[PDB]
Image (cartoon, helix red, strand yellow):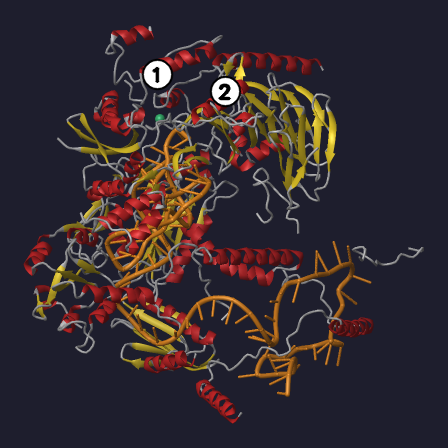
Amino acid sequence: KNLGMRKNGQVWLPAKKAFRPTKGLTSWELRVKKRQEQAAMK
Amino acid sequence: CTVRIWLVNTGRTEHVLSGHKGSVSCVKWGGTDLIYTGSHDRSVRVWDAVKGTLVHNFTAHGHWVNHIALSSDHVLRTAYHDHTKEVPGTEEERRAKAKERFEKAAKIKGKVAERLVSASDDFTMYLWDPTNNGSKPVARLLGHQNKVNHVQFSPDGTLIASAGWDNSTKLWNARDGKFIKNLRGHVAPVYQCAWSADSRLVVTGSKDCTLKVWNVRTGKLAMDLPGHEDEVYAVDWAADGELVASGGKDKAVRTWRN
Amino acid sequence: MRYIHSEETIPVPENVKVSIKSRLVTVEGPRGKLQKDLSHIAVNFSVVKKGVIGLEIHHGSRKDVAALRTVRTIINNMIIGVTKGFKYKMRYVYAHFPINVNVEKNAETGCYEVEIRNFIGEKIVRKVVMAPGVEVEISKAQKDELILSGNSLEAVSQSAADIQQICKVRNKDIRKFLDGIYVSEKGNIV
Amino acid sequence: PQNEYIERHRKLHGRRLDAEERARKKAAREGHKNSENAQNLRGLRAKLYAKQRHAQKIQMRKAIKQHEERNVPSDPIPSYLLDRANPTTAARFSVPIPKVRGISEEE
Amino acid sequence: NEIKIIHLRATGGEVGASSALAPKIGPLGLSPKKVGEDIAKATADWKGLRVTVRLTIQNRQAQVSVVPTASALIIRALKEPPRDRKKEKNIKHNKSVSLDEIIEIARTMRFKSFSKDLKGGVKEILGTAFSVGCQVDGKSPKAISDAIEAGEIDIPDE
Amino acid sequence: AGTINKPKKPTSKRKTTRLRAKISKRAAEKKRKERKLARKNPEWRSKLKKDPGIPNLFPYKERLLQQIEEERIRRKEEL
Amino acid sequence: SEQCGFSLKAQINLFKSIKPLFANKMVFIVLNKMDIKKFEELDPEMQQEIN
Amino acid sequence: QHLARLPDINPTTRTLLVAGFPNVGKSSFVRSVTRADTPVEPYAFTTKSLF
Amino acid sequence: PKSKRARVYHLTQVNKKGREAKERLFSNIRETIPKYQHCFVFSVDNMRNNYLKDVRHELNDCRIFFGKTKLMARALGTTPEEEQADGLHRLTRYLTGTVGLLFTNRDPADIESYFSNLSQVDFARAGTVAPRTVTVPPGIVYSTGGEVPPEHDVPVSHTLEPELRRLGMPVRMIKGKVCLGDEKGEASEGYTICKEGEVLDSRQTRLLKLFSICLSEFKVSLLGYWSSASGEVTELEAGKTRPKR
Amino acid sequence: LKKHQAKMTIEREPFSETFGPKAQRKRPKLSFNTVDELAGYSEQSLDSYHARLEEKKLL
RNA sequence: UGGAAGUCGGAAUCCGCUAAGGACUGUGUAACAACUCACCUGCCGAAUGUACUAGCCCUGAAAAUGGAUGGCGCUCAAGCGU
Ligand SMILES: [Mg+2]
């Protein structure tokens, strides 16, 4: 069973995930490398 | 809302007088070692300067207390200096001369009693004798049609001069507070007034950029002093009566002689 | 921007039979069956795994992608309704006039009927007809409580809202007159 | 009834049972309601609403700027003129308005 | 046979501190005038100062003690002239107190302080004195606290 | 509003010749007026406008800056 | 019983202070809370002042 | 609003006026003899207006 | 995206910490490393942890860190190349979840005896198994909910009645009193907050905290300690069984 | 003086500090200082009120 | 201040423990209590937040016989840009 409280009382509602329609296009490591390049160029 | 007492030789605070709810706008120190304060909380307080404790609290004014004056201010400002132009040799006899002058100026009915006049924004003034009357005012001085800015006793203690924002300087009997005469002729609010040493003359500096010297026994305008090109803020008469200093918004000191 | 592919997944418990044909979802469990026509939303249904239902949208806008979340929650609510059920507990409170609540089951229609009398001393008899599949019981554990139970969350909550809205205090100060019937608890039957 | 009778009733009997959740839901719908008012009101009512909301945004931005800058008289006047309401106070003998619109005799 | 602990705020040298206490100690069986006299006797050291008073109740007699607080200790150490509280209102604590008796107040308040060291206790007392509004060594207690933190002023250990 | 069940008088999108001519005349007059105000404009204007620069999301901005340094050093050496 | 938080001496003093307002009226001093302390339990001097 | 919530006191009718210090039972007496809903509480100045 | 949630600007004094707090934690841990002989790792799992202030006050000669797990692990050094002292990277395997560091100069036996003898009854958090059945009796609801008898108990405040209704108690207001059913204890049964053996949820634990009922215990479990003199990590009983990363 | 009494009172103490949710007024303004003065003022006020009622009844 | 404990007011607004917590963001109390927010930690898991600019769309003021993109009608246009 769930252990937390939902604010609107609809306890049957599932644990929703974030709405990210562009999820999975880029990786975390590549984004870290692009962060480093971006900071250096700036 | 505080009055601090400083020791001049050390630069240290000895007493802090607090209890006012508004800004203390005027402070005087009498010859009986009492400190008189007037404040914007509509009150006039008398404090014991030796102990730093409140003695009297007068709450009769209906607005800001702008200025207070003592009956012995002229002699307390100059101490032992007088018309002889000679100072006594030693400090003890100098202090004796200063105390003698203060007592001679402050005797009422043979008893030393300082008289305190307070001028307020409620268009009025109050006259107090804390030694003889306690918290009861001697009189309420009425007649100004606007706020009373400055008030001063004469050096002989018989007259009181008041300057108002109703373009007028008024004269009052210093014993019962009765109105005597109105010195009319300024056309903008009168900011300051100052007595001559012989109590014949009062000089008033106003917002209309002028000084006016008034003969108080005749009740007339003796002299008119133009020359300031802006508002006059501060006016003083020398204790020997030789010169009058004026200063204001025109940034230049002006000195006036006969 | 048009997204090439968007995917949602619905897990299905072992005691549930789900049949989807032409976007008409039929969900069957221990407590009965529920049916919902979802042909107003462009979605592709599939069986991506044993016990997982997949929802696809191809070449859809952001709004079309976001509608899949609503479809997911609706089907999950159908599954929860046929497995555990839905239950709304309502409490009626009064100051001076006791609220008289009678619950009957109509024979020819099969639906429950709730009659409310003496609401703030009124002589009228309020009657609310429940949605089909909703059972109403006057509680015995607590005081002045109704329990509305069923498989359809939509039907149960709408019947509760109908009971709540038929007893409105009118032209009186609502700070002073607190009389009414209110939803107190929401949950599952099991 | 006398004095704070609604407060006494509030203390003795509480609210309606749905008041807190109901007000929470209304305050939650307030954003959608503001957008619907911005896109749906007509005429002078819409103009006054837009002007009021513009003013609200201006004071909100000022308050946020002051809370950002939390962690960081003009002319000389005497002491008796201090704390009063004082004015701010800011050859060719040409008048400030040298030319105006002429008025014909027929007008 | 239980102990009842009651905390209150009292001014030293008055009886009327038990005016608000008498509603609740009445059912407890205590004498309001007796506990008021006990409070006045215990707070005769702290005349004119708002202090915290603890009453312990056992077998329907009260034992009265004064719990030291930093604000009361600082105001007492200021050595202000005596005054009548009904006529001298809106006072300000603008006198000066020395750093040595500030350290003494910190040593007194070590039993309440959660700080690891007397330097931290002294800085807490300096912050309390800053809230009171007095001066330390003729300067601002915030300035002495900053000097202690930067290392110009040293605090003895324990 | 009850617009769907009880619509009001329609607002005509059909223009009139007089209104079209008046609008065209007033537009031409406003154009001439703003030309005159631009001629008599007292506002300060920069001799060179502030250039926006290179966008940050451009992938080759850093190598372009490397180039820009190379031509400035080359021009300094040549001059 | 003095559980109100004020002394009975102060109660008599307040009554004597507001007595000039009580002219042309009728005055009844009601001693409440006899379930706590009776009038006879009070010492004779205070009873004498009340009388 | 305060005038709208003010009680109606007829100054020329038969009237009992209950006075004293706080916490002496004034509101308890008024509750026991009338139907007015004046609060009764053990702290001083529970009643802050005329009832 | 024009349709979006309006982000609330908080008009309060305290701002977000950022990277400065992380670097400050790094510097504090790296400066407290050379000053002590032992570094214990302790765990307080599914606990309120407000008694760590009392633990810090009682162990005034020790230094306690209770920051982020990954930040403390990176401060200590997770590999032998980046470790601050010899063998500290063996200690970082215990740093999972809710952990704390204890730098001490005392012998380890005193620390183990202190944390074995330290016992404090605490309010249970969600997920804890309820040790007993708690039932509020019918009638007038009191402050403790029936733990202390009502002749010594005080009636619960009338401001808690909407909160009790929100937490699921069918309480009502009768003449300024909060009552469960009827004032005479009729027409309703008692309200069972929790049953014995039932895993507590947050609503039930909130009800227990409002009624001041404690069903758990605050315990600090030592997993293992690193000694600088031998440069080595000794594991304890809790760290033997706890999972490691 | 009565030309400026109203603005003088408003400057001395504003409307918001006198009555309302943020009022700080605690002592009232009274025309009497003692209990005897209050009794005399009350009986004179009652006499004046009755006299005015008789005048309005006659009118 | 009758009472005022962060939360009727006025002015200051520091220190400790800190992982972090305002001499307090709101609810609440006669005053307390209690709750809540700022802030922090644990779970989770990968992209987000804010402000501006440019397009298209809505509002950005309307009276009075029944009517007008010329009319039907048109919605991946039979609308708009190239
Ligand atoms: Mg009472």
Eyeballing the image, is A27 above or below I166? below
Q: Which image quarter has ligand 1?
A: top left
Q: Residue I170, can we see it?
A: no
Residue closer to the observer: E23 or H1 = E23
Look at the numbered discs 1 and 2 and tell me whether their residues touch, using CB distance below 8 Å. no
Q: Going by the image, does C148 lie left or right of H1?
A: left
Closer to the eye: label 1 or 2: 2
Tell me where residue I40 appears, x and y as whole percent: 13, 63
Nearest to the observer: residue B108 or residue C106: B108
Give the residue at the far right of this rendering.
D105
The single residue placed furthest to the bottom in the displayed view is F78
Helix, strand or loop at label 1? It is helix
Residue at image mark 1: G10
**Residue C117 at x, y = what percent?**
43, 42
- Residue C24 is left or right of residue F46, and the answer is left
Q: Is residue B33 visible?
A: yes
Figure quadrant of the C terminus of chain C: bottom left
* Towards the viewer: I168 or C1: C1
Residue I67 in the image: state x and y as whole percent.
Answer: 25, 63
Residue D91 in the image: state x and y as whole percent.
Answer: 80, 57
- State left or right for residue I151 relative to residue I105: right
Q: Quadrant of residue C17?
A: bottom left
In the rendered view, would you say H3 is above or below C5? Answer: above
The disc numbered 2 marks a residue on which chain? B
For label 2, the residue is B100
Quarter of the figure with residue I85 = bottom left
> Where B131 falls versus I212 (above or below)?
above
Q: In terms of image quadrants, where is residue I14?
A: bottom left
How many neighbours does mark 2 have within 10 angstroms: few (below 14), some (14-19), or many (20 or more)? some
Give the SS element for disc 2: helix
